[PDB]
Image 1 (cartoon, one colour):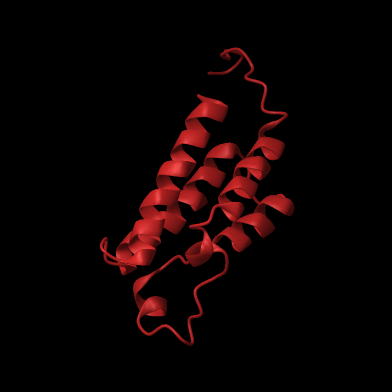
Image 2 (cartoon, helix red, strand yellow; image 1 turned 180 degrees about the vertical axis):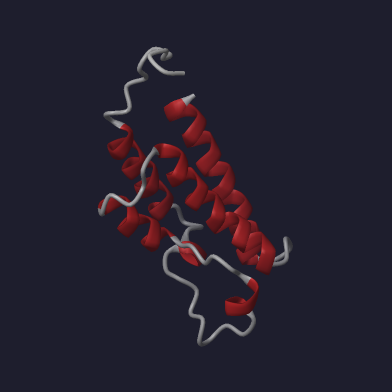
Length: 115
């Protein structure tokens, strides 16, 4: 509350460390469905169904330009990529499996770097 604060967690490396995580996600062999925005002209149903499209290149641009206020808003966009994937793709598909795999990969790096 006013003049009453928990001890200050050092967040000075968060930007650099999110960048590193994102580099590792970008280079994963199963990243291919997520590298670029889904083409809304060429994929019927995507624009209407997926209200907030997100992809690794959009996260990279937001990160590089100071549009994440804190490490949680970063995690929320990474998770959005996978939530969108699950919304649109059957579990028993190459893309559906890719999304599950990458979400696992992410969640471990997130826990190991920050928890």
